[PDB]
Image (spheres, rainbow, N blue to C red):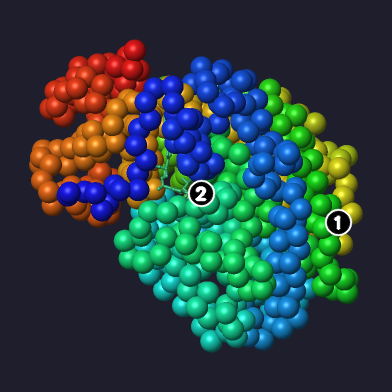
Amino acid sequence: MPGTKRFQHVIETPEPGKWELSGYEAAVPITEKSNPLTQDLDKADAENIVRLLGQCDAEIFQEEGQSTYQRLYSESILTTMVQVAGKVQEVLKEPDGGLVVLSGGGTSGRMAFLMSVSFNQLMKGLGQKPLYTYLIAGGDRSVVASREGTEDSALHGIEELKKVAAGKKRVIVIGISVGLSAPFVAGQMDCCMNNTAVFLPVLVGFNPVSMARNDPIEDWSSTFRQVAERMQKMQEKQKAFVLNPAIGPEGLSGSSRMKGGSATKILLETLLLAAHKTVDQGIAASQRCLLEILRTFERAHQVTYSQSPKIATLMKSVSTSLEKKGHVYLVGWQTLGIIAIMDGVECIHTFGADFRDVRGFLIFTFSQEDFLTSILPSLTEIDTVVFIFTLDDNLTEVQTIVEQVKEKTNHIQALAHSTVGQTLPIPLKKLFPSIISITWPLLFFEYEGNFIQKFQRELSTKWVLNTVSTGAHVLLGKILQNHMLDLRISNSKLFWRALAMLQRFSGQSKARCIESLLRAIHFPQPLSDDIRAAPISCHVQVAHEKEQVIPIALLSLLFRCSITEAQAHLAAAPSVCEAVRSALA
Ligand SMILES: CC#CC[C@@](O)(c1ccc(N2CCN(S(=O)(=O)c3ccc(N)nc3)C[C@@H]2C#CC)cc1)C(F)(F)F
Ligand SMILES: O=P(O)(O)OC[C@@H](O)[C@@H](O)[C@H](O)[C@@H](O)CO
């Protein structure tokens, strides 16, 4: 019947109470699952939120128990990390013809970029030709932009790969889809597999290959699962690899920017750092070299979250600036400024936030006087400004910018990374009464940029800003339990997520839930057969443009009413948050 070809794969809503017995719950991929720790994230205060998220983040480093999915510290994963590090060596031994590509949509593409730089630096510091590069869904503009819709084309991702692989002779291609979901990556890997002689695909993400996304891709004949299964087969001959540890669900469901992006870094820096540091030591990568790194990264979670009360306080002050109607500025030097940007831009699609709400700045990329003249005028009593830097930075430039802002804001806090017994100039650097100095044990680095110290710092920053920003908005009511209900459908994965939220919250049938969603999207056109049968892209292009689509569809379903009736019900409640919450009673 009209539709069956597009919604056939969607599991039926289970009957109340049998959500697990139905077998439904075991097919929700980990990345999309509801984390049990965050059942009530919408009733945690800023102190509980930092706890529960900091807890969630810890699950990256949990070990495998006794019938269970492989995790990061399991032997099959470390073994794969070694073999891959291995394959990165063959390419470092042969830079003429060689390339290494790090590719992802969204935050996976963001993490890819950062790492491609760091390891380019590492080879610059050694006077080696840089071999890393990156590919992001939507081209390089995508790095610092919200562009959710660009990940849905396999041919796109393939074209980008054909470009950058020029007339190279040996190309390692690392595809990063946290969900083993994004068509961008799917094509790249599948294509890699058609020319083994040149290419080596390494798929990275955080679901088992049996939860790999399996719906049809519009411009491609195989699904991610098929492509992933076939790579897993090629691993036995070392011509492809899948690195897919489980790290547990996200604190905010399907927010793979967070634990997924963290784990992407932890997992990839480790592996690559290991492969570098060990080539010119004349030695093969061992698990022992890897674990040195992972344990350092593990220490960093504990280092980072031991400043939780302060993290909670900064969040409170970001939540209030927004609760009024003011803005937040994340001000950062070097890489930690980029991460600031990427946290800000990510807030847009993740929260229906506007590009000023939580903005990032690198010294997007404005200079010292430049930022003084341009942005400094626009500030206000109620804002918040956050300063992000190490003591190795250049604090003459830093003190300047804060002194000027103190006048006009007085809601400033700060994030400062330091080796033990570095000291903060200006004994009256108060300024920041209650800093977040984060103080790093001296480690034994041999590389001239101290790249391992870099990653500790980047990650620690990412955890803070993720938790800050993500937390701020929870406090403001916009999260439902641990789901963002009212998201903007801007690619196919988000469309399915919306639909899955409808089935869960309403408990009503798959057909009914699809019908309500499609009506809410295309209102005032009614459901024709053309519409029912249309590719998910068509829905997305129309929904992406609209507001409250999901909450309207859910209301229609609960009240049993028309779209017309529920639009007027929405406009007759004080807020979307309150309408939805009480319809659920
Ligand atoms: C409240 C509620 C809810 C949503 C939820 O029921 C849920 C959330 C997301 C999903 N997804 C959303 C994403 N789809 S997917 O096809 O895009 C996909 C993505 C990645 C992947 N590895 N496999 C499939 C897969 C799956 C579905 C559906 C419909 C399913 C259920 C759960 F609670 F489990 F979080
Ligand atoms: O890395 P994945 O699973 O392929 O997802 C890629 C992107 O959808 C993802 O990065 C998204 O943009 C972020 O908002 C996640 O919160």
Mark 1 or mark 2, which is nearer to you?
Answer: 2
Q: In the image, 235: left or right of 452? A: left
Please report the residue visible at 73 percent of the width from the left and 39 percent of the height from the top: 66
Query: Looking at the image, how many numbered discs can be counted on the residues?
Result: 2
Residue 121: in sight, yes or no? no
Element type at marker 2? helix
The residue tagged 1 is 288
Residue at 47% from the left image edge and 30% from the top image edge: 21
Say the numbered circle drawn on residue 211: 2
Image coords of residue 195 (percent x, y): 53, 81
Question: CB of residue at label 1: within 8 Å of ligand 2?
Answer: no
Q: Residue furthest front?
A: 21
**Image quarter hosting the C terminus:** top left
Say whether mark 2 is within 8 Å of ligand 1.
yes
Residue at x-position 16% and y-position 29%: 563
Tell me the distance, in whole angstroms, between the alpha carbons under discs 1 and 2.
30 Å
Whether residue 280 is visible to the viewer of this picture, yes or no, is yes
Q: Which mark is residue 466?
A: none
Left or right: where does residue 426 sit relative to residue 366? right
